[PDB]
Image (cartoon, rainbow, N blue to C red):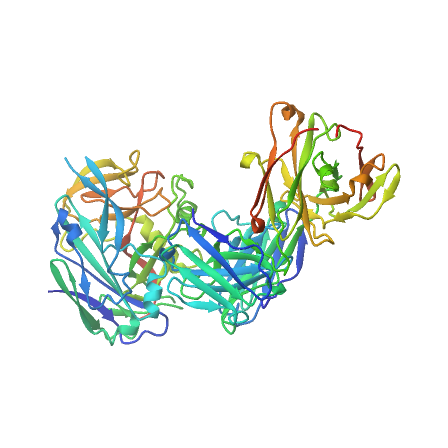
Amino acid sequence: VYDMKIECPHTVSFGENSVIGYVELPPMPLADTAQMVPESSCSMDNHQSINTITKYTQVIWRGETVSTEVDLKGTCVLKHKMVEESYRSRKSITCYDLSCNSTFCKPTLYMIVPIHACNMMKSCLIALGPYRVQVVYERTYCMTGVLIEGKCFVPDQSIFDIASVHVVCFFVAVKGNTYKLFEQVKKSFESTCNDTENKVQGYYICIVGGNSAPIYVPTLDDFRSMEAFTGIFKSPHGEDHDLAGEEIASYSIVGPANAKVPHSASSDTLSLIAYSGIPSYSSLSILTSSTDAKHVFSPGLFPKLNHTNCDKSAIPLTWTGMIDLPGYYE
Amino acid sequence: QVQLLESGPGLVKPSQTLSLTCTVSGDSISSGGFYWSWIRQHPGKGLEWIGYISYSGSTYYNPSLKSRVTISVDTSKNQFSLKLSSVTAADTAVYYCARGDSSGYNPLNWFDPWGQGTLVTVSSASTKGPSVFPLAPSSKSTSGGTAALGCLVKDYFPEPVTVSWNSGALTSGVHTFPAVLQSSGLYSLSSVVTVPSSSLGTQTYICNVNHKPSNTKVDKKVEPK
Amino acid sequence: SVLTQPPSASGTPGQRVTIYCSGSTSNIGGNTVSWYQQLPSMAPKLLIYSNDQRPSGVPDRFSGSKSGTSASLAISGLQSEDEADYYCAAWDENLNGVVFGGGTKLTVLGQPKAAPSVTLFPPSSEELQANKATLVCLISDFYPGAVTVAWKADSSPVKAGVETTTPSKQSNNKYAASSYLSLTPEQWKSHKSYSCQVTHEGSTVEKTVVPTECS
């Protein structure tokens, strides 16, 4: 019986905020992934949160990568207005991401709950395969401040006082002229790209401090959205290398390897950097040149994310990071 | 690419119920989370939003037309439908379907993309398939070895009809003119195409004329006399 | 139309043309504006959303903004192909719906005075077999868009039987119009020649046809 902490402050101070609580797990072997099917009493969503089955291109590396059109369950592949229509009905969302070497798979489970349930949902249980997990809500004595290493921090609207706060981002795959995210990538990083080698359309949705209204990325006139964009794309490998007990970095960087996405591809659509040892970097991403978000799972591989060259690349699905915000204490 | 496409009868008589259907493509309609919307535009007039429905069943109609408007949904078949009851001569318009979105949390804010629309004309009269005629290039229209020829489309109701050339292979240098509301209550138009003289003896030019409210599909060949 | 737009705005290439949209607190005061450009007789197209954002394939010549209950679309660097109709749209809560402005007819002036291209077609060998005949006159690629139509026969004009449509801007910033003549075929070959005359800016362009050709 594991535990996941949902951090509730005493008050919310208006705003349609959702709280996020996530925790990682001890691992399981490689080929066990498909067995994982979660049950819950606090998924609460209309068959959309837990029942996330997605067409992936499993890249089994050997030796030598093997692309296979596989189907995965429980991933954090989010959809348009998912958080929103979850909020209006006071229902929840839950997903998990994976960091996998050639042999093992460390999970990371996020749960997203509207703040309208810091009192109703005081405790809960959710089971994922070999692990039960009690979802424990936990009150801090903060009014609305997020608890950051002993102090209650409160954005915004003010000398100025400013700190760095945690933020969780998930990619939402939506198609339309207004979602050409790679165009913003080019306009704000001066990489040598164009619109055909990079066609995936979508955006990111993020929550800050475990209690915040969602932040869409990118939007030009949002201070926090552009902060998140800078953070996400200056470290797409995730701004937290160290998973639960991986400070002594043993990255057997095996090296670059090509793969098809999907398996039926005529040539190699994705470049990767195979590794082994300790799984710390996430293993779920999305292929870039495909208009449809053709999701990719890569065990024992760091997919190519550096967009210095604008072809045969991938973008992360989830991302946990830190960005700068103005606040107050006492 | 995501595209919306409208379909329905071009003519609906007064005091009937008008049905139209928009089909989505490129995006899965259940991956939408969008406000799927019907909008219309009277001839020479501006825009007016009819209503929307969400992928669950939320019917949000314009207060003016909520009495008459019904909006069907079909999640299993990627479609939604409009059913405006008690139509009169006032409701004649171009009807567009749109994928209205709402950026963040607030309701409908913008429409992207759009279907290319369909013209529903209302009049208690009936439909007539037009008649197509050639308009030959004689020795009267050349300027430097280049001239033009035409296809006449005559005596139809209601709008619209369409004329293309060479099954779409001929696009550049083709111009078609607005139809006319004659005193006879009939519409007529013409499609002219400009080409050099060279191809009068080794190339063919056929215009294809279509009229939806009458099922009329005519491939008419234009040659010098 | 709850949102109030100016009816028409106009300019010349290289301007900064601004188009307005004024509503109340119930529509623009609390919800975002989107901007739409509709080209001549075409389905609309999104230009601005979230009051300033640009879709892909939108030039920053088009910027947008909104303050209080009133919004503006700023075409900084006006160009020729911007001759269209501009609508503003926003969500009104007291009406619980989406409202459009009255549209803004934008005219790009400064284009030079032009001469009309006149085309004339006599009835076909097919149409003369249907108790009817039709002669057609085409006026294309002229500026301004005003016309006067005069049909003649042997230096002597005629008036009736001619249906003439309103002139139309094309996609290439130049204007065109059509003139249709329907006759009993007896009076198609009861006169020597038929001539079409286009009057524009004072001047005239003329064309002629005869039936003694190969029928």
Along the line of sight, the residue nearer the viewer: A211 or A34: A34
Give residue A327's position: percent from left, percent from top.
Answer: 34, 67
Relative to C158, is C51 on the left or the right?
left
- Residue A18 occupies which quadrant of the picture? bottom left
> Residue A213, can we see it?
no
Along the line of sight, the residue nearer the viewer: B147 or B208: B208
Along the line of sight, the residue nearer the viewer: A247 or A98: A98
- Residue C207 occupies which quadrant of the picture? top right
- Residue A114 occupies which quadrant of the picture? bottom left
Along the line of sight, the residue nearer the viewer: B145 or A321: B145
> Residue A179, can we see it?
yes
Q: How many marks?
A: 0
Relative to B189, is B164 on the left or the right?
left
Above or below — where is C203 with respect to C89?
Answer: above
Above or below — where is C190 with respect to C13?
Answer: above
Q: Quadrant of the C terminus of chain C?
A: top right
**Residue at 20% over, 39% down:** A274
Give residue C62's position: percent from left, percent from top.
Answer: 55, 52
Give residue A223's position: percent from left, percent from top.
Answer: 40, 59
**Residue at 35% over, 65% down:** A84
Above or below — where is C152 with respect to B112?
Answer: above
Relative to B87, is A73 on the left or the right?
left
Q: Quadrant of the N terminus of chain C?
A: bottom right
Give residue A326's position: percent from left, percent from top.
Answer: 35, 64
